[PDB]
Image: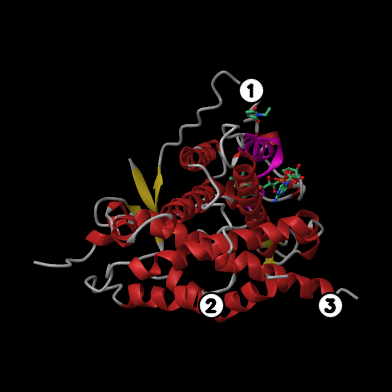
Amino acid sequence: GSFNELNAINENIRDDLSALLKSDFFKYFRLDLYKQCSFWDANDGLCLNRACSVDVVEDWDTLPEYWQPEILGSFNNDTMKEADDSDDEAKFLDQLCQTSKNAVLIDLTANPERFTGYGGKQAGQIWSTIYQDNCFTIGETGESLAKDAFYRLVSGFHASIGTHLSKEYLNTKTGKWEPNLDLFMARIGNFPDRVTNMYFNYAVVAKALWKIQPYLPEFSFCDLVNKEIKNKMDNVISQLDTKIFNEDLVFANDLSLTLKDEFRSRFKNVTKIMDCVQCDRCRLWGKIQTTGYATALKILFEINDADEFTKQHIVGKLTKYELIALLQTFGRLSESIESVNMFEKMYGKRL
Ligand SMILES: Cc1cc2nc3c(=O)[nH]c(=O)nc-3n(C[C@H](O)[C@H](O)[C@H](O)COP(=O)(O)OP(=O)(O)OC[C@H]3O[C@@H](n4cnc5c(N)ncnc54)[C@H](O)[C@@H]3O)c2cc1C
Ligand SMILES: CCN1C(=O)CCC1=O
């Protein structure tokens, strides 16, 4: 139901958000070179044999080398620049401009989240782990809800990826990246709740962005390149305003104090397992999108029972790294929400 509203919000906002997410400020993300998957130790089953790491959609053998998952889900060298202190990604928003007197940068706009062929049992297990580490301390005041929230979140993040991989599928025949209505239906379409969870997430990440807007410092005016950027982001955050934001989508007002952090743990601990993803491009976004939600949560759980002086520390002293993650995640969510509609039509003009 409440859908429709987000669909309008998403429409009057898509053009500007994209142009924003392409800006120099938001077009690069810092990614750790070496990946340490702590899970392939005292073995549980994590399949690394290429046979079980590929979605059995296309018949890969019957395809060229340069079309194998190994290539579809790999960055494009030429783009990724060196990561030092120049990418203030580590700084806090409150310290980007003067108020008074082991990794690299991946060009995001160049490595869009799409169908890479990655899947199979390896991918199945990953997802499976995340859904399973949904177990907070019982007895706590909010036990249940925390998981219905957590689960819901992941589930959307899951659909978010699925949608993207269907809107940007590869025509194994013509060799043109195009939408795949059938696949969209098999993964998302025929499962009402999955489409609903993406909307859920959109409302969370949007409400998170909204909540902090009033506190975003003047972080970009001083950078000769991205001047407008801060203001151009306010502009967006504003058109977002909704009645939905009155719901406590993430049970902030009902969750335990200790319990909350626990909820945050599962996430930095998901964003971690993201190193067990052998596909390079899937890992990238799984690490952005996950840090995204993790940040959305930090924002919501704290702005909650906080005064003005506090809402200051919080937002201002939040890393550029996190703001890219957040907005970038809202970017995926924005397009997933839209590809849904763009598919209901495609499905409509079926007969
Ligand atoms: C972090 C991560 C990032 C990935 N990124 C990409 C990518 O960018 N591009 C690409 O082509 N592939 C990507 N994949 C792979 C993709 O998510 C699938 O696993 C894959 O396409 C193979 O699909 P499948 O049908 O085997 O299982 P999936 O469709 O993953 O199914 C896993 C199982 O979970 C259930 N399930 C599916 N969706 C949901 C949901 N939303 N909520 C609750 N349950 C669900 C299914 O019923 C099934 O039991 C990624 C995997 C991980 C773990
Ligand atoms: C079997 C259910 N469960 C998990 O999935 C992890 C902790 C727990 O008790």
- Which amino acid type is shown beneath numbered disc 2? Ile
**Residue drawn 50% across and 31% down?**
37
Dot 1 crowding, Cα within 10 Å, few <14, some 14–19, many 20+:
few
Give the CA distance from mark 3 to mark 1.
46 Å
Q: Secondary structure at mark 3?
A: loop
Dot 2 crowding, Cα within 10 Å, few <14, some 14–19, many 20+:
some
Mark found first going from the N terminus, 3 or 1: 1
Q: Nearer the viewer, residue 9 or 58?
A: 9
Q: Secondary structure at mark 2?
A: helix
Q: Secondary structure at mark 1?
A: loop
Q: Which residue corresponds to mark 1?
A: 44
Q: Which residue corresponds to mark 2?
A: 13
Q: In the image, is 268 to the left or to the right of 342?
A: left
Q: Which residue corresponds to mark 3?
A: 349
- Which amino acid type is shown beneath numbered disc 1? Asp
Q: Is residue 61 above or below residue 101?
A: above
- Which amino acid type is shown beneath numbered disc 3? Lys
Q: Position of residue 66 (x, y in %)?
A: 61, 51
- Which span is picked out in magenta? 116-132
Circles 1 and 2, Cβ within 8 Å, touching? The answer is no
Mark found first going from the N terminus, 1 or 2: 2
